[PDB]
Length: 49
Length: 439
Length: 49
Length: 49
Image (tube, rainbow over all chains, first blue to last red; front, top):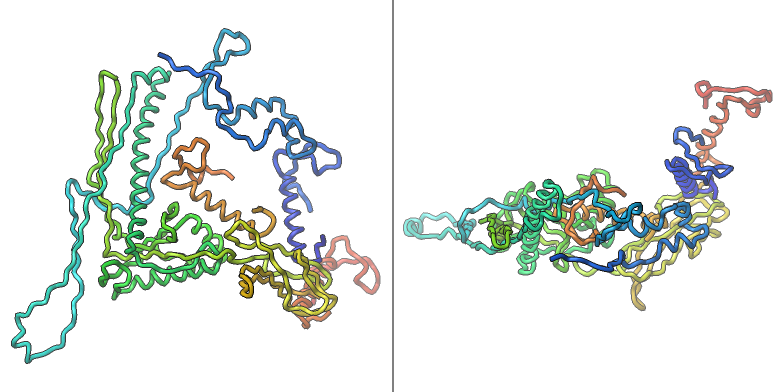
């Protein structure tokens, strides 16, 4: 919605980012987050925000 | 002499909410799309739950051969009674336990004129006794046909393991029966009504009731533990005192979980809000109002008189019989303190929590608030939202969307309330959140 | 109710799961949690959520 | 707005100053914070408030 609108919006954004990072780092892999759909897995130490 | 079964379906006593193979087969972008690339999914679906009846299957290469059993596993489990620590010593063959107690006496005025005449006056020590009788005599019986059982096993190790499993089952049954008896003792005492009753609200209802029950329990234990004693906590009222290390509080798993999640987690200095006595968790009580019982370790009077195991052999039938005889005395002592902590009726609606209490918003932002009403009934109750501290132009809708006015500098107080009373007699529960304004 | 709809629902789910695990791990056993209705018992270290 | 009018105003001022210091101490530098409009760069140990 908006990061600077309210504390609730900020914490919602934080939760969404954490969930997305965990989904990216899920070991079995997924093809939902890359430009061309290939089943790939990423590592948490390699993620830059 | 051979037992056989014919035409037994795999789904013997299984009821299906839905057909998973049908859901997989007829699916277009639903949650079942991940199982589509699975090749042998039908076999897994139809066998993975396990089968209850075995049937001979010919292998697919040479149909004259029969598939064999590869692995056999024996499942073993051990059971115990958590109240076993309350058992007293062991009496070999005695009966009719006698418990004797001498009480305090009265003080007399000093005198010398009547002390030359009342020298040999008598004053009885004012002693009282009570009795306990043996009241449990039972046995567990089980038979083993080893000679006929040999045909169902190929390895002597598995045979012996299966043989020992039956003895283990006997012991588990004895343990669970002992636990049930020792739990039934408390319910029988409450039915007789010899507990000391304290009326409390439902601890599971709301957070205020839980903390009030905590206060009552702590105060009760404290007033039990005074050196001068009292007569208000034990049947056959007599002057006695207890020690803090000897006080046992028996509660429920749901009560433990609610306390741990509500009070202890949010409470700094747990030791100022935790239970004082030794806690013991069981699977609830049978009484209609019992919540938690605070007793002394001397309250129990459980003794075991006989624990014997015997075996007999029938050679005509070629089998063994195992008998486990248990004789016990199960009773309680009325000279020990015992408080019941009983509760009354529970209200339909207890409390409401909307959202994280502290929020901060700008002068042009919007906020979303949820709601949760702790209702003891399946029926849902509507909520109404309002704002108390605010200027003109700021408002909250009925769905839980709060918008701030163009310009204001104050503290917002959003209140969500539920009405559960009758006509011309409202009963409102109040839930409040604090919202701050950042220019 | 819902693990995500509201924080009250989330904490109620937490309490329910904790109570369920505690009553699963009871020394006297129970028959209310398995498909064969046998008097079985589980250990806390053997439970996976 | 005002450093002493309200707690919200004070914390907004704190946020603004922290952001300003962070963007002043940027490795690539900027020319928006000096009267000469020349791309320079400062350091946190040298900044004074």
